[PDB]
Image (cartoon, rainbow over all chains, first blue to last red; front, side):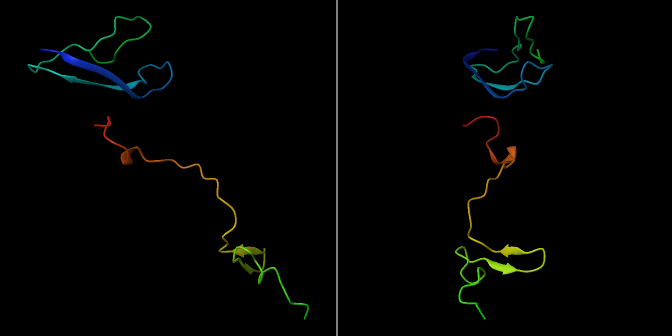
Length: 49
Length: 49
């Protein structure tokens, strides 16, 4: 991993849903890796980790 | 014989009035409200990039 230039764009969402939110995180890495996707919220969770 | 301007023949939309339930065919009349389901396939992948 090396993470730089991170942005979140939400393309579409279902309002306050089970996992009805679809968003894309576009990014730059200096070294490709696998980075954990996350939200520290308890009123929101990311489906994937 | 009082055909000096039947509505078919002066139809100001070029409607070919046709008979039986009655209809005005191939007009230039109005503007048409359309609720159109756009295919998601005809937008970009997930990002304007």
